[PDB]
Length: 221
Ligand SMILES: [Zn+2]
Image (cartoon, rainbow, N blue to C red):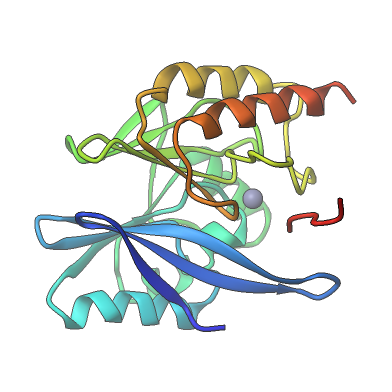
């Protein structure tokens, strides 16, 4: 299924790429393209080199140069395009924790890394926030202050925590509480697979996290 690009707000697009899960079916993965000063920043990179190339070239050829990409966590649904981006010397970014996990997993790393609670990828325009470990030990979210849009990625799991292989279920509630207190002001929250929502996704996630500690989508009901 082809890469999709849909307008979310002025200068904010959702890119949707797709992975086949053999024992289930096809799953959508959302990232963003954010336009700042007629220049493009990737928020998460499509699974494959081919879709990353397609996305990038799509913007570049029409006059919006790719300035960089930020990957929100180490899973390939967020980092699959880092190889291609690096091969073209397009700046790639990910936290130190994310790069360390990529290194351990024998994956190509972002060329640029950062640490701390807040990192401004683009001053006043694109902020990276680390709420603490959750869906993965390294997960971060990306805040766009001008549109009040939060890309939550894999941390935002409003309707089920999903793959717990790499999750920190002990810390996830505290992290989710922090995120919720931090970005209750968001107008839109963008999860990796679930539908774009409002700030209510922050609370649902918390609930999930909590319930989880008490111990693809699942459509059976
Ligand atoms: Zn993940």
